[PDB]
Image (cartoon, coloured by chain):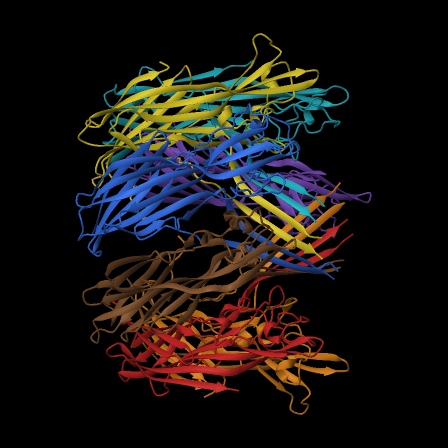
Chain colours: A blue, B cyan, C red, D yellow, E orange, F brown, G purple
Amino acid sequence: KVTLYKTTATADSDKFKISQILTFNFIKDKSYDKDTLVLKATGNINSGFVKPNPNDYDFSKLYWGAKYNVSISSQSNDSVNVVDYAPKNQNEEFQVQNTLGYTFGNTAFSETINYKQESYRTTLSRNTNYKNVGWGVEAHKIMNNGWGPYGRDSFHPTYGNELFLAGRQSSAYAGQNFIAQHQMPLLSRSNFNPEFLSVLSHRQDGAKKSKITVTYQREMDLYQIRWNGFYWAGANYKNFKTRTFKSTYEIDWENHKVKLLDTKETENNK
Amino acid sequence: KVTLYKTTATADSDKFKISQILTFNFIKDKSYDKDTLVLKATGNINSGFVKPNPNDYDFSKLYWGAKYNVSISSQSNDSVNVVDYAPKNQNEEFQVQNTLGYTFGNTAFSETINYKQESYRTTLSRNTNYKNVGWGVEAHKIMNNGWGPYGRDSFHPTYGNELFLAGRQSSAYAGQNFIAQHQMPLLSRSNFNPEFLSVLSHRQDGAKKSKITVTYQREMDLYQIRWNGFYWAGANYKNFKTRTFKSTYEIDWENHKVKLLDTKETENNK
Amino acid sequence: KVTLYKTTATADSDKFKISQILTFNFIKDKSYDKDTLVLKATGNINSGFVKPNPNDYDFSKLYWGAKYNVSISSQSNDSVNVVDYAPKNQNEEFQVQNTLGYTFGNTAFSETINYKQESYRTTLSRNTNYKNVGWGVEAHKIMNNGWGPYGRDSFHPTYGNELFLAGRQSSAYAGQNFIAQHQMPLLSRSNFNPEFLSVLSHRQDGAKKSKITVTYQREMDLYQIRWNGFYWAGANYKNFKTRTFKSTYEIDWENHKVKLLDTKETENNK
Amino acid sequence: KIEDIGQGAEIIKRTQDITSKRLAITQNIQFDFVKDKKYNKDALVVKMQGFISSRTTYSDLKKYPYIKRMIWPFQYNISLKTKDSNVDLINYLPKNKIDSADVSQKLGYNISFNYSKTISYNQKNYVTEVESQNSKGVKWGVKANSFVTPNGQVSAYDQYLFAQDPTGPAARDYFVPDNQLPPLIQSGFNPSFITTLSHERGKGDKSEFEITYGRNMDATYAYVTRHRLAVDRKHDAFKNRNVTVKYEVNWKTHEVKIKSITPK
Amino acid sequence: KIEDIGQGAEIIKRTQDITSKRLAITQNIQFDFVKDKKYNKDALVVKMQGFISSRTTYSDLKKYPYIKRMIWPFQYNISLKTKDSNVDLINYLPKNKIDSADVSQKLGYNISFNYSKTISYNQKNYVTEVESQNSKGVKWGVKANSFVTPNGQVSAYDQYLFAQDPTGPAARDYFVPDNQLPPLIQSGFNPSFITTLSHERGKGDKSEFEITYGRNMDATYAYVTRHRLAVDRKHDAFKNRNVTVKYEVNWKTHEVKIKSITPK
Amino acid sequence: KIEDIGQGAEIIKRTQDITSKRLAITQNIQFDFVKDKKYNKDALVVKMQGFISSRTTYSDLKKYPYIKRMIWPFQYNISLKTKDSNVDLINYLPKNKIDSADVSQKLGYNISFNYSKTISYNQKNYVTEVESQNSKGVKWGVKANSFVTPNGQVSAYDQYLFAQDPTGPAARDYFVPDNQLPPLIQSGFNPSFITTLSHERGKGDKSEFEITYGRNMDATYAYVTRHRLAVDRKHDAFKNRNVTVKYEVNWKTHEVKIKSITPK
Amino acid sequence: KIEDIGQGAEIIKRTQDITSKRLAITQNIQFDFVKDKKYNKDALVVKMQGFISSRTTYSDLKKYPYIKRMIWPFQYNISLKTKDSNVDLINYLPKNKIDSADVSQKLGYNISFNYSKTISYNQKNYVTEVESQNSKGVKWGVKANSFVTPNGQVSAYDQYLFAQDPTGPAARDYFVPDNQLPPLIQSGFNPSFITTLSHERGKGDKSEFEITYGRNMDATYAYVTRHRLAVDRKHDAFKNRNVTVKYEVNWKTHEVKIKSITPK
């Protein structure tokens, strides 16, 4: 028989507008020689979007949320290891159709690749070990309109990064030469609501009490435009501001209850 | 447990050709502190179509059913409130397929919106409160043939509303310059069979007997055409005749039986 | 009350790189007057691909695996017959759409056959009898890049078989005028993993012990190219080398256990 | 994947309906107390349903009656908030989600070099976005997105949206007919959001939540000048027109009451 | 209402396998005695399975070796017959079925008139047709239909089918490569037909059925002459090459044995 | 119809996870001892899961710093091997499979003959191929196949793959942005392979298996010379960078231990 | 969320079949008495099935035999009626329903503007419309809609429908062959309507319903004059050709007995 004792724990950072909703299921099975805990981390990492000021003549800047990193970790001294995690990395696939045709002459060839484009992609962190799992949602293919795909590092020789630039040769204050908030990807100007899962496990022959450190962080980027006199140009400076909220939650394997211990709000403006 | 004592009630108005078939399920559940009654209002609101007279030289008119309003209400003094209702309002969706293509030149941009067109659309009445729910089936996109989609309020400068006008420059008596009954939308020339649902709820501590007023009404529009000497024209006058049949049904929550009390047929010709 | 006793048997040939994984299910049912055994012959027949030597001026050759034959047999003296087998031969189907058009002139016709093409095709062996079943996976339609479908016996007057020839008029050592291992079909350069099924049946009145001979073989073809001075030409010599591993497995119907007896590795080079 | 979600047991359901005739907003909230034996603390699933009438009104301007105006709803705002420390939000729905589009890239050479790219998406008339979620409360706002009109889809931020060549002197005639108005603008919006609020047992008995339903209405002013229809849109003309009902929940007697409602 | 038919209940299954090495035809017939309590008489579901090898052979005419020939199978004939009055066929499968095609008719007027009609169908390499059915026995014949070639589908009745420009003096070279030969011609055919035979009880004990598997082989003769290649096809070159196994069924002891096989 | 070993029965699951920080490879292997009453011998389903970090590094060459390089993973190699005579592999997954493509051939005569052939396939960024399977052990290798890039799909064997016109003096700038890198190259690979190992009871008590996870990394060197970007690729720059963990399974006490791991 | 009618419960079924050879109309009505314990009153599901032969007749006119005519069915009328206050209709099927069509609007600019709109629908040869429903009885009429011809769909109201260039002096030859006639015109119509009639218990024992099946037949007269073919159609030539069967239902003894039939 399997017995699932469920409990929940929550932490909040009003300063950085980051909330952590953690759901826990303490599955106990005789077939396993260890205890198992499925942690489902949900909640809200606000984008931190700073609207461009409309009274800016030649130079203006916006701070947009570009990467949100959620990491669930365990202490090195404990026996609590991380067996499984989701969403895992994906071997993306695409469908290709090649056509060869001749008119007895107009020999013609054609190749169509059908794929799926997303504005943000979740990948695992290269620091995922036996005691830590991490995921990073980074901006991928952001389309201005029919103009794009662009990203945090695209570059045109003359006009530079044109990610959020309304018109290359328009005539308005720089504050109003950006695309409106409505055309920007949802996660870039609004809340990111994570739905990540991790399966921790602890040898029953261990300390009844352990601690797990869950971190929710946003990495804001600065996009600035300028009028060189002839054309507008843009630049995306990555990880300008890093707002991180880390929380330690004491897990009692004996009584199957989780209690938040300490909360550490950290800022890395650069 | 749950018991669904079911009963039915019917009222008729031969004068206005309007019939009301009301089905009732008195769901009794211990976990709900109140009684619940699901009312399924079905029946028939005849369109009231008046055929155009074929011996009309320059001017002719038809009266077509354009809006059918069904409303289930409860008295303010009772504790019977309306918890749920269906069909609710809809956030309609559509599919877009923007394509951009160039030939190394013919830069071409195409955009396709795929949607669904209905001749009549059901929406909630803006007078839906805690004690009344209403629905209105109004004429939406009516296509003459490959012409339109016209509606009760379309307008062309010269020819005017051309909803049921056969030919703009035809040469027949006005009575025969209309589209035939077959091309006209089904609901406009035939019976409307409503299938609406409402859930009512009454505090057990309330009076054993309550009354509910169910109203079925048709709104007829007058479509008239005229020969100005050079071209035919058309005009749709909305809500010219409003034939309404309202019926009060005493609901006994104690014995789970519904009895029709009074039947009021009302006409609002204008 | 059907009862199933499952067991497994394995044999290996390191020299020819051929492994046999045989799974056996001894179904016993009162409704059948005979015993039944389902044999699932999985395992691995390596392709035996010999890479072309890069330092070859005008003439070079590769040995590619073109046919893999797996055959499960029983002795003539025993009562063990083969009732069923899978994959059976297939009556392949195709979808045809014919269009006749006219313009009022350009009378046009069109015929589209939609089918499915495979690099290798499994068929039964014409020596399948009541006491032996065989299957042969032969190379079918191998496409160079967009050039093709080719096979082990295609022929062009001038250039000959151009199955694995990179360029007809290229200028490289013959060793480097072949398509790279990546473009070559998977089974031709990598392992072939069989999944074949056979049902055997033995009269209960028969001897408690019987023997079954399972054979896994590879037929390798030699593809050689040469520079005649003006154009490259190619030739596929079929069945040059045949590496066969046959194994006898004693089946005890009484104790429902299978034991490998002898392992015969045979090589036929021509 | 392998996650049971704080639900799956006996539910005692209690329903409360209130209506503000002044703002035409109705709140049909159902509070279902869940008692999962496996869950450590207490839990209440609060289902927010009801009707927020669009209150679309077409009328001429007072001083200059030759100028007409349409007050149409832009964003319907729905929110649940708690000031009690014991109660904490553990699950909420619709949640903000990433979006994807099917793309097709074709390169051809008619030995010309044609290239073609088709991006396909599924748009909705109004999009629901989680404006702000904290442990105590959550807010969602159904802002307008795109509308299908004859001659192509039009963004909800276009100034010439819902305006047409005047067909007469009446205000309704300066704006498109009802056959070209989405159901949410013509009639109203029916919310369907679910919020599970867990409460630590032992430290509390009564808890009060304020549920707010509302409408931010934009206005399009149109008038014919020098023979050119001039359309202008005042974004967020009247904002924060909301109704707030404070409901007191006694976890012990499984009874929900209504403390007070503003606008009264 | 629909219907039931001899079904469910209990089945005693007996299997007999015979092989004619001289004609390469194998008969794996399973005889499943059914005892439906609801059915008045007795019943035996006879499933015909096995392998009829194509025996495709490529040679040169004896008197004129410059002329080559391909004996390829055209129709595989499968049949079950009985002479016992008590035994009667009550259900048989594959049955002859009517066919349908999806059609599309378009009329356009680019104000030039345009008309186009597309008829679509699903062809099969070999089609099975019930040649003859009477109460005592049934016969099916899998005749050839259409084959896909690198240049469009070709009927199985074309004279230039399975022949190509000679690639060498060998007979196999005058005919298409094996990669362009359907599996039924390259290897063989596996029958899968089912026949339920009812037998009136009280009037009989033993009954004998003769099951025939066979092949009608056509031959294409090809030879290069006067700067051309001449292909000719002798329809039904060798016909009725069949094997007949007579099986004796004792309904009482539920035992099927094999009386005689011809050709022995 | 072969059912399978391990069907239903009872499974005692034991999980072991180890991490090599020096090579960034993690092995989360779950060993599920199966006890099918119907199966004659003992059986252990071994599920290979974990994370092999891509370790993609962009850096300038030491001697000549004007030349930049990208060490990117080409093939992730996963393998399980045993030296114990009693233990034999009975089922493994991924298994090398044959491939198929939908083809359409159209011939038309616009009385001007026109022929057209469309072959359609489904490609994956990385393809898993069984490199070597013997009774004792099995090895799979996830080699790279094709990558969707702007302006068409590109083979993983192209020399100018993952290189772009330099956007600045930094090494990362000589190579395509992360938005155009598959997730397996940007981050890492998660194996999901299953191996069932049977062990003859009576002649054995303990058994040891070495499970190897690894990466073969190719390198692309790029530098701008005489106004032409020059890209070159050294296939298999660093090969066989793997971590091997020997696990000792005691079939009797159903306990798995880690004997040793290399790289230590 | 409504259970409705008599879900489950117990049904005593009684079937009555009558045939009017004079008008070729057959009434196979099944009266299933439902006894749902939850339902307050009594209920009878009446399923109307049968065969109304088209009686399509092709003949020359009496006075002028050079003029030919085709009496073809236009609307098959089916109706059930009660003259007893106790019995009331509570559910009826097919019901009149609103219709929808998938639309597609494309706008292009080959930098030459392009616009295209495709509306798609699913037509039926004959459409069933609820002519009149009151508490006592319901009437449905299957009027003709559209018919596929070798040259595009033709409305059923076209005068030149079902007429062709004369192929001989026989009347059948002035009209299209049977291969171009819908099955309902060639043969007949099979009704499948369901009506549940509830009856208040205590105030009644016996009740009588008249079920009418019928045909309204239009006629197309065609004759060749002055090197032209003159086709004319008399809409509703013969109307109301129906057969009415009065059935007396004793709710107490669950017995339905045919009182009288007209045309006798």
Q: Is residue B249 visible?
A: no
* Relative depth, front residue between B179 and A125: A125
Does C120 appear above or below A58?
Answer: below
- Residue at the right extreme? G226
Does G163 appear above or below D16?
Answer: below
Q: Quadrant of residue G230?
A: top right
Q: Quadrant of residue E9?
A: bottom left
Does G73 appear above or below D26?
Answer: below
Q: Is residue B22 visible?
A: yes
Quadrant of the snapshot with the N terminus of chain B: top left
User: Which residue is drawn at the image coordinates 40% and 39% (left, top)?
Assistant: G46
Query: From the viewer's perspective, is A145 left or right of E193?
Result: right
Image spot of residue E48 (x, y percent): 43, 73
Image spot of residue F130 (x, y percent): 42, 67
User: Which residue is drawn at the image coordinates 48% and 57% (left, top)?
Assistant: F72
* Relative depth, front residue between G200 and B22: B22
Query: From the viewer's perspective, is E231 left or right of G239?
Result: right
Q: Quadrant of residue D135?
A: top left
Image spot of residue D22 (x, y percent): 41, 14
- Residue at the bottom extreme? E63
Image spot of residue C81 (x, y percent): 36, 80
* Relative depth, front residue between F187 and C10: F187
* Relative depth, front residue between A104 and C29: A104
- Residue at the top extreme? D63
Total number of numbered labels?
Answer: 0
Quadrant of the snapshot with the C terminus of chain B: top right
